[PDB]
Structure formats: C-alpha cells, structure tokens
C-alpha cells in the first residue's frame, strides 16, 4: 500500500502457499507438478515486489493533458 | 543444444518457466498478447483433427509448439499489466494521488508529490512528458539486472 | 529503495558509484551509503579475491 | 461459390469482425469526458461527444460480416 | 514411477544377452513394439 | 546569441538522428543481402530446410529497429533553444550506434555466408551456426546501451 | 517495442481523427483496416520471432554454460512408424 | 532578420527536398538492373513464370514512391522567413530517407538475381525467396517513418 | 566563458565516448567474423570441435565489455562546466582503449584461424592454441588500465 | 592564461601521453599474429617441438611493456598549469616510442615466422635465429632510452 | 523501342530547363535562387539512374 515493510507481509503470504503446495500436489505427474508451479509463482511475485514506486526521489512528470483553458 | 551426461540434471523446468517469462517481459501489449493467444486457442481446440491432418510446410513447427505460445501469451499479458499499456493507453484502474495547482498553462514543468502509488503496477502519472520516460527507463534497467 | 534521502541530510548516492572507490581508495567510499560498511566492504573484497 | 473460405472469404469475415469490438469502447470513451483524446493543448477539441462518427463507422462491419459468414456457414 | 526433474535422474543398466537363436525374430516382434530397448553394437570393425 | 547556445546548435542534433538511423540501415542491408544470396543459392539442393535457414536475416533485422528507436528517442528532444551540449551529445550517441550496427552487420554477413555452406551437408550444426553468429547482436546492442545512457543526461538544464 | 507501438498509434489514430461524415467515414474505415493489417503482421511477427530467439540466447548461454557440464548419448528404442511418398 | 535565421535556411530546405529523391532513384535503378540482367535467362528457360517473376521489380519500385511522398511533404512547407532550425531538420530528413532507400535497393538487387535462378530448378522456392526480399522494404520503410515525423516536428516549434 | 572552461570543451568528452566503443566493436566484429568462417568450415569434417572452439568467440565479447567498462565510466564526468583539460583527458583514454582493442581484435582473429586450421588434424592441440591467444592478451588491458588511470585521476583539479 | 602557460598545452600533453601505447601495441599485435601463424603451421607437422620456439612472440611482447612504462611515467606528471614547454616535448616523446615499437614489431613478426617455419628441417637453426630476433627487439629497446632523457629534461629545464 | 525510351528520358532535360530559363533575372530574391538548381539536380540524377538501369 504505502509502507515498504508491507513487502515482507505480502511475501510471507505467498511463501505460505508455496510451501503448502510443495507438500500437496496432484498425483498426476506429481513429482513435476509439485515443482513447476512453485517456480511459476516465484518471480511472478518477486518482480511485482519491486514495482513499488514509493520512496522516490526523482521528479514526477509535468502534466500535458487537462488543457486547463 | 546438447544432451547431458549420465545422471546430469536436465533443465526441463527451467525451460518450462524462464524462457516463457523472458519472452513475456520482452513485450506486453495487451492487444498483441491477446491476439497471439487467440491463434493458440484456435489451434489447441482444432487439434482434434489437426493432429491427424497434414501439417503444412509452414505449419509443421507451428503445430509442434502450439502449447508454447499459450504460455508465451498468458505471461505476456501479466508482464504488460504492470506497464499499464494497451496500444499506449491506460484507463487509470487504481488511484495514486498527484498534486496540481488550481490552474496551469502548459509549457511549464509541474511537480506532483507522492502520497502513495499504485499497489499493483505503475501509476498513470508517467504518461506525461520526457520526464516520465527518463524515470521509467532508469527504473526498468535495474530490475532486469536484478532478475538476471 | 527502502530508505529515502530527501528527508535525510545525506544526499542520495549515485545509482552506480561504489566501484572505483573499492580499488583506488583503501576503503574510502565517499558515497556514505553506510558508515560501518566502509570498513567492511574492502574486507569482503579481500576475502573474495584471496 | 466465387469466394469461399479458401477464397479468403473467411479472412474478410474475421477482419471485419474485430472492428466493432473496439469501436464500441472508443465510442464510450468519446461519450465520457476522459480527456485522453481532446483535453490537451495539442489535441483537437471538437468536444468529447464525437462518438457518433465512430459509431457510424462500426455499422458497415456487420454488413460484410453477415454477408460473408452465411456463405462459409453453408460451406461447413 | 518417474523422476522429479530436479534431483532424480534417469537410471538404467546394461546386460549380456543369452537369447535362444530360434526366437530371434519372435523376440524382435515383441521388444520392437515398445521396449525402451537399444543395442551396444558389438558388430564393429566389420564390412557388409 | 549567448556563448551557451549559438545559432547553429540544433544542426548537430538534427543530423544526429539521420546519421544514427542511416548507418544502421546500411549495415543491416549489407548483412541481410549477403546472407540471403547464399541461403537462396544453397537451398536449391536442400529445399526441405529452407525455414530453419531463415534465422540469420530475422536476426540481422534487429539492427534496423535499434536505429529506429534511437533515432526517434533523439528526435523527441530536438529544439533550437537547446544547449550546445545537447547538440553534440546527440550526434555522439547516434554515430556510436550507427558504427556499432555497421560492424555487427558485416560480422553477421561474413559468418552467415559460410554457415549455410556448413549446414549444406548435415543438419546437426544448426546449433553451431546460431552459436557462432549469435555473438554479433551484443556488439550491435552495446552501442544502443551507450546511446540511451548518454541521451539521458541530455535532458538536464541548458544553463 | 513500447516506442514502436506508441509511434504507430500516433501516426494511425491521429490521422484517423479527420472529422468528416461524407468522405471521412470511408477514410477512417481504410485507416482502421490498414492499422489492423500492420498490427497483426509487422508489429507482431518480427517482434515475436526476434524475442523468442533472444530468450533462447538468454537461457542457453547463461544456464547451460555451467548446467550441462557433460554430454550423454541419446536413447531411441526401436519402434514402428509410418512411411509415405518420397524418393 | 535575426541572429537565428539567416537567408540560407531555404538553401538547406531545398537541398533536403531534392535529396529526398536524389538517392531513391539510384537504389531503384540498381535493383531493377541487377534483377532484369538475370531474369532474362530464367524466363527463356521456362516461358511460364514471367508473371510470377514481376515481384522483384515491382517491390523495388515502391522505394521511388517512398522518396516521392517525402519530397512532396517537404515541398508543402517551404518558405523564406522560416527558422534555420527547420532548414537543418529538412536537410537531415532528406538524406536520411534517400540513402537508406539506396541501401535497400543495393541489398535487394544482389539477391533478386540469386532468387530468380533458384526457381528454375525448385518450383516452390518462390514462396521462400519472397520472405527474404520482404526485409529489404521493411528496412526501407524506416527512413520514411522517421522522416514523416521529423517533418511534422519541424513545423510546430518555430520562432520566425 | 573563462579560458580554462571554454564552450566547446565537452565536445571532446562526447566524441570520445562513442569512439572508445567504436574502435573496439569494429575489431571484435572483424575477429569474430574471421573465426566464424574457419570454425564453420572445420566442424563439418571433425564432428566434435564445436565445444572446444569457443575461446575466440568469447574473447570477442570480452573486448566488447572492455569497451563499455571505460565508455560508461567517462560519462558521469561530462558537463558544460568542466575544463577543456577534462576533454583532453577523456579523449586520450578513449583513443587509447579503442586502438588497443582494435589491435587485439586484429591479431586474435588471425591467430584463431591459424589455430583452428590444425584443430581437425591435431586433436592434441586443444590447449596449445590458447597459448598465443592469452599471450596475445598481454596488450589486451594496457589500454584499459591506462584509460582507468587517466579518467579517475584527472577527474579533479579544475584549476 | 599566460603566454608561457596557455590553456591548449594539455592537448599536446594528453596526445603525447596516449600516443605511445597506440603504435607500440599495434606493432606488438601485428608481430604476434604474423609469428603465431608460423607456430600454428609448424605444430601439426611437428607435434614434438611446440614449447621450444615461442621466443619470437614473447620477445615481440616486450615492446608493449616499454610503451606502457614510458606512457605511465609521462602520465603521472599530468596537470593543468603546465608550461607550453611541458606540452611540446610530450607529443614527440610518445610518438617516438610508438613508431619505434611499430618498426620493431614488423621486423620481429616477419623474421620470427620465417625462422620458425624454416627450423623444422634443420635443428640447429634455432640458436641461429635467436640472435637476430633478440637484436630485432633490441632495436625497440634503443627508443626507450632516448625517451627517458627526453622526459627527464621535460622538467630539468623548468623555467615558467 | 528502348532507344526511344532513352530519347523520351532525354527530352526531360529540355522540358524543364526552358521553364527555369524563362524565369531568370538580374534582381532575384535569394529564396528563388536555390529552388531552381534543386529541381534541376533532382531531374538530372533521376535521368541518370533511369539511363543506367
């Protein structure tokens, strides 16, 4: 939201699902299904974890639309 | 590329995951990804008879990896989602909050302070002048290195 | 990314400036990212290279 | 028939089909005052209520679609 | 009955065969369908 | 005018984008032509493998888009009231990218000429062809990296 | 990709914005058709073709450099298959 | 008259406008020549594919159209009181399109002759060779796309 | 402006940045192109030399990186306020690195071609080729080190 | 600025500093390749004598060291306020070593290759060619000493 | 007929030169001093390329 410590809170929630699924996997091709999704979600989250634009020093773009006649 | 020696780990899962995510992060236009996935869905649903019908010269490899383009696109749409680009457009899904005066005439640099950006993706505020581009490029050239 | 710099007296160090210092200087960082880090960066480097 | 799916009639049908799908949303955007097409110093300012032109444009697409789909459906 | 694609690899073996000569074609029909079978060509350094 | 901004400052920026696109265009054209001639000559006796022999030209095409993107990026920051700094750095980046692209184009063409002959006998060395020729795009792209790095500083105030 | 998409959008939609209901609608139709022709063909095919092979680079020369530190010969069980017209 | 826009801005404008066609002609001529020189024997061998053999020359022609449109657009916006800035812009655009088209013509010319003769023995190499030759015009179009927007930019930002 | 900080001083800084990578990219491209034809010609005969012929192609990339490591370093010292001295010190390093890299690329391609020529005839000589290749790298950093010495040193003492 | 210490002397200073490395390195690389071709040619024929004929390249590899030592020795005396006398000498000093190294590299590169190629027939030709190659490299040596006192008097006669 | 193609190409050098010659004078605005040679050079080079091909 606005606090960068929220990253740890939203990280632990996904890590819990990851560890839970590592144990619970469908029996159909279980030994590869249990390992695929856990990586399909890893960066899936990590690259989102860095999208946070907060704590930004650089200036923000001047406005161009909203003509304001 | 080459076979591995005896009892040498094969990079099956790395191929399943990384290469599609790489291709997705290559480009993420919503329309382009959706359109590309349209052909993938058509091919996979018609595979009932395509599997048996003759594969054209240009269609041999295409039919070979019909299930790959699906992953390509399903990751491309997400990768572009954080970029908030649909043919260079954005509906301002979330709200971030930005400061502007009561009135302003263009041609002047206008500063807007941050009180919290989009929880997911980047805010629409970077749709302005070259300042937005020269911030976005610096932002993006770092995450690539980190992820690599 | 975590710690801001406008509110802090220390200005934001350059995106990539901690490279030349590790070699020419015996530990002088000149970017002031962290005080104690100055005396341990060269130490980490010397374990790495040895 | 003179033009069929192998005569690229199906290509014409699919080409015409995917026009209204976005002309509808662009007409909605014009109807709304999203100022993402006219509310700028450089953008032409004829008023957001110009969705009538785009809506008119969307009309002809069904003309091609319905005509060219019936023949191919007869083929299948 | 497979590998995990992370740590477990393929594990296999080789043997010396002592098959009867008369069932060579008989055995071939069977193992030729799907047997995961390959031969170490001892018939080397020989001409047609 | 002031020594900061003489009259003909924007001339350099204007010529920069043209040169940047143009050198890359020359390099890409040379490479693609010299490769395609060989590919089409060879495929006659190996026509089955035409499609897998097309990778070199689609590879070489990227230099053109590199030039286009750098040229448009430079053009976005053109003006007559700009700083003479912002007249020279533009041409510097443009010529860097152009010459890098030209070198990459020559290398790719030279390698591809013999690659197809090598593959003309057996299909194994497809990987070898790609591996040998896949070290030129890095050269061609380093110019783009440095160009975008330089032009970033351009935006700073003229004073 | 971002820049090329932006420039194509700018040179297509703005041109299409010509306000005229007597001859402008047909011009908009033609521009709309060519915009699709280019979006599907040249803003997708070449880009994806380049992207997949660049990703193949980024995977191979990075992982396999220290991953496939060895080579093993292939296994190919003898099995039946179809044959058809040929030399 | 000011220190910004001397009288030889129209010099640059006119030279750029002329250059917009001064080169494309050379590339088109080179491509057409190197295609026609070889097309003759192949047509002689099989007097049935000349219609299918028109693709190279026609595809080489359109670079001339590329040059023509650029020249006409530049001519639309020529004057004498314009800022020298605009003159420099037009000068750049002209050559940028011109010898880019020249490079495209040189590239297509060398490959047209190779492609035509291949068909004489491989009937279905026709589809193959067109893929290769497309990239020539794909390259050529970039000069036009950059130049049209450069010309557009040359208009709004003016001072005299 | 002051005689020590003229208006055209950063022109040298801007040009040198491009030249430093240009004079290395051309050399790397030439070397890799020369090696590619030889490796492609040889691999078909002896079907195992792909993996054990990777040295020169990666040394080309090393030269390419050698370009960037110096090119980027000089960027942040540039500006409209530094002295003409800054431009001189920048261009000196740029030309030094560029020409040293060019010499390295010129030698490496020829030596690699010669070495791979006998590769299919001396399966023993799978390390003796690297002998000269590394011994040919004796000058591969002299330009780099002198450029680093100049840049980080003369980046001060404005007066 | 003053007449004895103008602002454009650092141009000559920097060119002199950076010119010594260039030509010496070029000659070194030229000799390296032109001789290593001979080693590669002889190795297949003689896979027995492959660690006893590397003298030519290594001897050709010392001129680079010479050019580097002179270069850095000049460089460490780099500063803004220098007399025009300071900038005058350095360019000559750098170019002298550069071209002397180039000249030595050419001769060593060709002679070492010729000798190593011809040595495969008769064994004793090795010691025969050693002296001529070492003298060829000594030719390069002779430039450095002159450069030395050149640098020394670049400041031993300091006036203003 | 290719020879008459060449002749028709050559006619261009006259059908244009006469026009510009018709509009030359002593006192001329410098703006209308370069456009003429701009047109002439373009026509000349186009003719040269056509003839070469």
Image: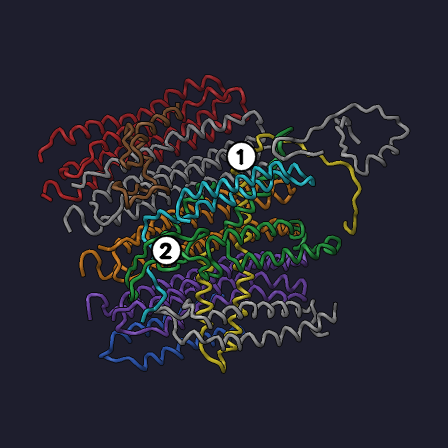
Chain colours: A cyan, B green, C brown, F orange, G yellow, H purple, J red, K blue
Residue D1 in picture, x, y percent from top left: 73, 74
Q: Which residue occupies 36% across, 25% down?
A: C46
Mark 1 sits on what residue? G65
Give above or below for J156 relative to B125.
above
Quadrant position of residue A26: top right
Residue J120 in picture, x, y percent from top left: 50, 22
Mark 2 sits on what residue? B132
Q: Residues within 10 Å of mark 2 (few under 14, many from 20)?
A: some
- Pointer 2 indicates a residue of which chain? B
- Does mark 2 fall on the same chain as mark 1? no
Work out whether residue B134 can be spotted.
yes
- Give the quadrant of the N terminus of chain F: bottom left
Q: Nearer the viewer, residue A2 or H105?
A: A2
Q: Residues within 10 Å of mark 1 (few under 14, many from 20)?
A: few
Residue F149 in picture, x, y percent from top left: 36, 48
Give above or below for J116 relative to H143.
above
Mark 2 element type: helix
Q: Nearer the viewer, residue F159 or K34?
A: F159
- Give the quadrant of the C terminus of chain F: bottom left
Distance from label 1 to label 2 (Cα)?
38 Å
Quadrant position of residue B40: bottom right
Mark 1 element type: helix
Going by the image, does J65 lie left or right of G78?
A: left
């Amino acid at each position: 939201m606005s606090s960068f410590y929220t990253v740890v809170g939203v990280f632990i929630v996904v890590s819990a699902m990851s560890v839970l699924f590592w144990i619970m996997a469908p029996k159909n091709n279980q030994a590869v299904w249990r390992s695929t999704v856990i990586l399909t979600l890893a960066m899936m989250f990590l690259m989102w974890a860095i999208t946070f634009l907060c704590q930004l020093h650089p200036l923000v773009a001047p406005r161009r639309s909203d003509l304001r006649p | 590329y080459g076979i591995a020696q005896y009892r040498e780990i094969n990079a099956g899962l790395p191929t399943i995951v990384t290469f599609p995510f790489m291709f997705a992060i290559m480009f993420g236009d919503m329309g382009h990804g959706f359109l590309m996935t349209l052909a993938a869905l058509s091919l996979v649903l018609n595979e009932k008879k395509i599997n048996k019908m003759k594969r054209g010269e240009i269609f041999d490899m295409a039919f070979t990896g019909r299930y790959i383009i699906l992953l390509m696109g399903v990751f491309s749409m997400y990768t572009g989602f954080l970029y908030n680009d649909i043919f260079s457009k954005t509906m301002t899904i979330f709200k971030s909050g930005w400061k502007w005066p009561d009135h302003w005439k263009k041609g002047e640099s206008i500063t807007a302070t941050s009180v919290g950006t989009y929880p997911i993706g980047l805010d629409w505020a970077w749709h302005g002048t070259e300042n937005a581009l020269l911030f976005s490029n610096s932002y993006k050239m770092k995450l690539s290195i980190l992820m690599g | 990314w975590a710690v801001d710099w406008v509110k802090d007296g220390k200005p934001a160090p350059g995106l990539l400036n901690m490279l030349i210092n590790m070699f020419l200087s015996p530990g002088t960082i000149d970017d002031e990212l962290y005080p104690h880090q100055a005396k341990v960066q060269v130490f980490l480097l010397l374990m790495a290279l040895v | 028939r003179p033009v069929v799916s192998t005569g690229k009639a199906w290509c014409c049908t699919v080409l015409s089909a995917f026009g209204v799908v976005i002309l509808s949303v662009i007409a909605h955007l014009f109807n709304t005052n999203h100022e993402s097409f006219v509310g700028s110093i450089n953008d032409p300012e004829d008023g957001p209520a110009v969705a009538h032109t785009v809506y008119l444009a969307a009309l002809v697409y069904l003309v091609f679609f319905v005509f060219c789909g019936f023949q191919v459906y007869l083929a299948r | 009955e497979k590998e995990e694609a992370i740590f477990r690899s393929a594990e296999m073996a080789l043997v010396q065969f002592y098959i009867p000569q008369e069932i060579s074609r008989d055995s071939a029909y069977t193992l030729g369908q799907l047997g995961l079978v390959q031969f170490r060509d001892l018939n080397s350094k020989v001409r047609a | 005018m002031t020594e900061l901004c003489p009259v003909y400052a924007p001339f350099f920026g204007a010529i920069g984008c043209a040169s940047a696109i143009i050198f890359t265009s020359l390099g890409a054209a040379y490479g693609t032509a010299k490769s395609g001639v060989g590919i089409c000559a060879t495929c006659v006796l190996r026509p089955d493998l035409l499609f897998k022999n097309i990778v070199p030209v689609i590879m070489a095409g990227i230099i053109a888009i590199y030039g286009l993107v750098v040229s448009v990026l430079v053009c976005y920051s053109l003006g007559q009231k700009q700083a003479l700094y912002t007249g020279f750095i533009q041409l510097g980046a443009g010529l860097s990218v152009g010459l890098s692209g030209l070198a990459a184009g020559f290398a790719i063409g030279i390698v591809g000429d013999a690659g197809v002959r090598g593959s003309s006998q057996q299909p194994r060395l497809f990987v070898g062809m790609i591996l040998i020729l896949i070290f030129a795009e890095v050269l061609g792209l380093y110019g783009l990296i440095v160009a975008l790095l330089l032009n970033s500083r351009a935006t700073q105030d003229v004073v | 990709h971002a820049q090329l998409s932006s420039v194509l959008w700018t040179m297509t939609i703005q041109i299409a914005f010509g306000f005229r209901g007597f001859v402008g609608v047909f011009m908009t139709v033609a521009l709309f058709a060519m915009w699709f022709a280019l979006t599907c063909a040249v803003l997708v095919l070449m880009e994806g073709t380049s992207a997949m092979l660049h990703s193949l680079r980024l995977h191979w020369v990075e992982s396999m450099s220290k991953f496939f530190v060895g080579e093993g010969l292939p296994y190919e069980p003898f099995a039946f298959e179809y044959k058809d017209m040929e030399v």
